[PDB]
Amino acid sequence: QDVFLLEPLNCFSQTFEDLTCFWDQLLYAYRGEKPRACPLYSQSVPTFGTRYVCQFPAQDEVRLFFPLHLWVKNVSLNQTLIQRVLFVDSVGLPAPPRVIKARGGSQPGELQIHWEAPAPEISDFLRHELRYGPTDSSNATAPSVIQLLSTETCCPTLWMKGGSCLVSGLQAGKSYWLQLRSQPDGVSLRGSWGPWSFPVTVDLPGDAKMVTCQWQQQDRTSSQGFFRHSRTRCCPTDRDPTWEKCEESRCHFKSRNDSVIHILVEVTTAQGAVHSYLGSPFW
Amino acid sequence: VFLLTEPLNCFSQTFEDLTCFWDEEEAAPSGTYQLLYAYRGEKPRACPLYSQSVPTFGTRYVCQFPAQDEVRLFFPLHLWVKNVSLNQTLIQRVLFVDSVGLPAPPRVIKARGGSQPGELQIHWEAPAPEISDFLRHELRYGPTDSSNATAPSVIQLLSTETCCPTLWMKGGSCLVSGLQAGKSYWLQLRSQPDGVSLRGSWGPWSFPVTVDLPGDAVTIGWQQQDRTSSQGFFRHSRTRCCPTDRDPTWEKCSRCHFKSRNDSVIHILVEVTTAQGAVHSYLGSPFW
Amino acid sequence: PACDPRLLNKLLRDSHLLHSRLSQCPDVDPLSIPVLLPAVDFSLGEWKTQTEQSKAQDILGAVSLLLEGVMAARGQLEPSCLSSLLGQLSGQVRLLLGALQGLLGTQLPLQGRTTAHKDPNALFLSLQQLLRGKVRFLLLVEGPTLCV
């Protein structure tokens, strides 16, 4: 989506540290004080109107949980113009998550989305959501499926601020482009859903007392993988996945008793591409 | 406990009282020994000091402050021995009473065994006046049947949750699991200050209190033994709140034939009384 | 507003980060003019004898006096790294005050004991204490009592 297209007056805060009000000067006041003019620039565009936009200096002026009164004072006759009373608390339009670097770890349909939140100081308040669609897009922008990022035990905003999640339900196969957007929860901070992220073309690794994994490779291909001994301590992981060389269809490795196995079979052709067969974990 | 790093280590049990000392191996005659205190720039006062000659370890000089309201959280406390004539100072320390307190352990640790099969409802009454909301309590549950040279001290930090401490009736009762069922555990709780508002080392453990924790359902089977009077002293919990009231709030029924109810957890508590009148109760795993 | 525990934790964490960042940044020499800072020593004894209203006005006065001290503090710190730090601190205190006024109510501000401090480290420490002492205790013990 677009940062400006998200109402006589429109305002939006992407980090609750900066605010930007626009329509189509822009005098604003915090409770009781002498009004000041927000620095305004004219973004003239033939398609739309004049599109007057100003950005607050983001210095001790985006104070939260305070009523802000906006009145437009045009230089024509200083008459009454567009007005809006807003809570910078309650008009948040948070920036989308960045550095998504999502990988299809854990379950074969599972997609780990460990992201570095662009705003690290408010990552607790924001309630993110994602939209993921197939690269083919057989129905244009019809697949707007959205999974809310609640604070479950497997999708929290863990540190190294950033966060992580374990959104599931994504079918195995074609690489999925996904954009996350952030909106304040509403319990303390309120606002509209943030602009969508840049569509990142992440992929998932398709589909397929010692245990032998009897797998066969196709013609003119390779055979390699890793095995993560995460010991199911926590659902999410850090940015760097664990790497463990599959040293011998006859791969042999030592694993903890009654522990989960994060198996992976990776096939790369002569040209060089990602083509993997992932198997479900076993206890 | 007194001795439990700083030679002037201080000791606060309720954050309304302070007491500290200097450890001296050499015995000295009474006199020219006082402990002075001055919150920031307050006029220094002479703490009431008595000499305690610890046997085979030296002579302590513990003193206790006169009144309890004179204590104050969030304030630098300077403890120096400054003499115009003697010009001698033994130990130096500047400290905050909420950065050093070793608050008292809970006094009564009534444990009813909980509702879960292997469970321990520690409904302590929080002897600390108004800081039961700012003390990360610990516990040292461990059986007394084995007494080795090294005491096995299992530790749980009692993280505050929706069904754990910081509740009124002050006090608190947090569900702690992982204990052996029916092993007649004993346990004691320390009170480490929260680390955010109040800071300091762990206070002394409590008096080890025996807990007649009921056994598991697998240990009982309902099954009846010879000369046993079993009572169906069950509780019909409606999934309202995991922590239980301080009083033993519980329900009561050949077979009592309790009627099942919707959207509630069915708890069965088996109470067995022997010919001697001793309670030999076992618990069971709740079901939907 | 301030009812959210995550808001209080975020305020505490941000104040702690600012305090840590002040130490790294050099040239923190104190100014001759003092900065008036609130009265943050709470005696555990006078916490049952004070009702909700008195504690509310005391905390509001504390946070407001902290804001006035910081505003003077920024004015004190010549535009520099240590002003950027004081600007971030002023933002922190303003956020806390705005959160408190939503739940606890404006009521009537009151003035308590007056303390004078010299170095900005004192400002950061006192803000950390306010988010550790009276504010933390009122928001953690009288939470359900006062929010509704």
Image: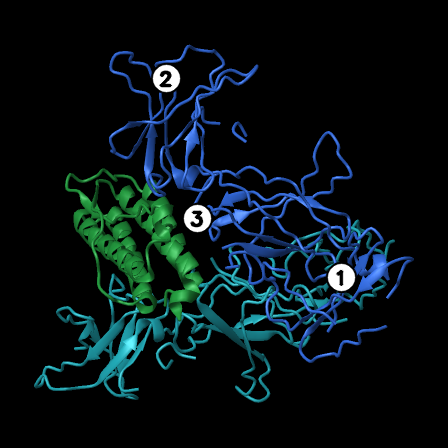
Chain colours: A cyan, B blue, C green
Estimate how packed mark 2 is, as few (under 14), some (14 to 19) or many (20 or more) residues with alpha carbons within 10 Å.
Answer: some
**Disc 3 versus disc 2: nearer the observer:** 2
Task: Please tell me how many numbered marks the rendered image carries.
Answer: 3
Estimate how packed mark 1 is, as few (under 14), some (14 to 19) or many (20 or more) residues with alpha carbons within 10 Å.
Answer: few
| Percent position of residue A268, x then y | 70, 64
Residue receiving disc 3: B196
Residue kind at label 3, given as amino acid type: Val
Instruction: Tell me the chain of label 3.
Output: B
Does residue A249 show up? no
In the image, taking residue B223 as reference, residue C142 lies left or right, namely left
Residue receiving disc 2: B33
Q: Secondary structure at mark 1?
A: loop
Residue in view at x 29 percent, y 88 percent: A48
| Percent position of residue A55, x then y | 26, 71
Q: Please tell me whether residue C77 is drawn above or below residue C95 in the rendered image.
A: above
Image quadrant holding the N terminus of chain B, namely: top right
The quarter of the picture where residue A110 lies is: bottom right
Image quadrant holding the C terminus of chain B, namely: bottom right
Q: Please tell me whether residue C49 is drawn above or below residue A110 in the rendered image.
A: above
Instruction: Tell me the chain of label 1.
Output: A
Q: CA distance from mark 3 to mark 2?
A: 36 Å
Q: Nearer the viewer, residue B38 or A230?
A: B38
**Disc 2 versus disc 1: nearer the observer:** 2
Could you tell which of marks 3 and 2 lies nearer the N-terminus?
2
Estimate how packed mark 3 is, as few (under 14), some (14 to 19) or many (20 or more) residues with alpha carbons within 10 Å.
Answer: some
Residue receiving disc 1: A222
| Percent position of residue B148, x then y | 75, 32
Instruction: Tell me the chain of label 2.
Output: B
Residue kind at label 2, given as amino acid type: Tyr
Does residue C71 show up? yes
Q: Nearer the viewer, residue A27 or C3?
A: C3
The quarter of the picture where residue A38 lies is: bottom left
